[PDB]
Amino acid sequence: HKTDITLQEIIKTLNSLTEQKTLCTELTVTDIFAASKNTTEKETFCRAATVLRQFYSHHEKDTRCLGATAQQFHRHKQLIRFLKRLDRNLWGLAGLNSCPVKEANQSTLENFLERLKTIMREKYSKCSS
């Protein structure tokens, strides 16, 4: 709660940098908004962390949309895992401690970005400072 300049950037940053650095594959990724079933402040975030990881691989594995070989596949993997973990741990929103990954749902990564972007974009744009 004390910090904010963290998610504030991650939002606007990734939100603004959509076309820039991003893999073009559009994979079905569970929808976190699917709270109309079973979502808790712990699990909800956990699942979100998993989704963020998948997306994080997009905005951090290609200059624009060319490459994605089996080579870096195992490399950039540690980069995202480390960065994501560090970021997620920097704020500590999930306040959890690592959890299993499950896709109780399915939604094109594109659809997720549209929903996430819409909220996140209208969230930070609130000018908190």
Image (cartoon, rainbow, N blue to C red):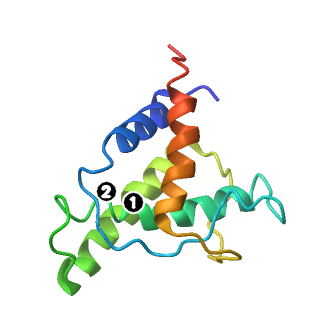
Q: Amino acid at mark 2?
A: His
Front-lying residue, 59 or 106 = 106
Image point 52% across, 28% down: which residue? 124
Residue positioned most to the bottom: 70
**Residue tagged by mark 1?**
56
Image point 26% across, 79% down: which residue? 73
Image point 51% across, 51% down: which residue? 114
**Residue tagged by mark 2?**
59
Q: Amino acid at mark 1?
A: Tyr
The spot of residue 13 in percent (x, y) is: 35, 38
The spot of residue 46 in percent (x, y) is: 65, 62
The spot of residue 61 in percent (x, y) is: 25, 65
Tell me the SS state at disc 1.
helix
Q: Are marks 2 and 1 in contact (CB under 8 Å)?
A: yes
The quadrant where residue 57 appears: bottom left
Classify residue 57 as left or right of residue 126: left
Tell me the SS state at disc 2.
loop
Question: Relative to 8, is 31 above or below?
Answer: below
Asked whether residue 56 is in view, the answer is yes
The quadrant where residue 128 appears: top right
Asked whether residue 52 is in view, the answer is no
Classify the position of the N terminus by image quarter.
top right
**Distance in Å between CA atoms under marks 2 and 1:** 5 Å
Question: Relative to 62, is 114 above or below?
Answer: above
Image point 19% across, 59% down: which residue? 64
